[PDB]
Length: 25
Length: 48
Image 1: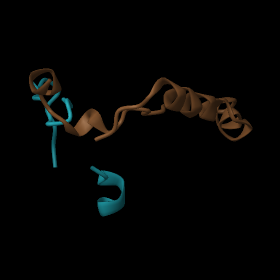
Image 2: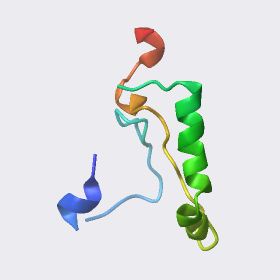
Image 3: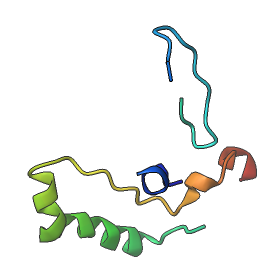
Image 4: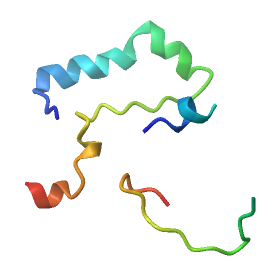
């Protein structure tokens, strides 16, 4: 819900995503 | 969760019309979730 307050390695150049409960990829 | 009467949602809108917010826009676009927090009801389609 608020990632910015709580938190104040590598991702591939070709990936698939999936949908968050809050419709996020 | 909240649903709005017309009169309410108009009030809400005129809110972003207020001098305060206007100046925010003049520098940076504004997003305004004026949804009654229904974002948290998943499968709302189904609920209704």
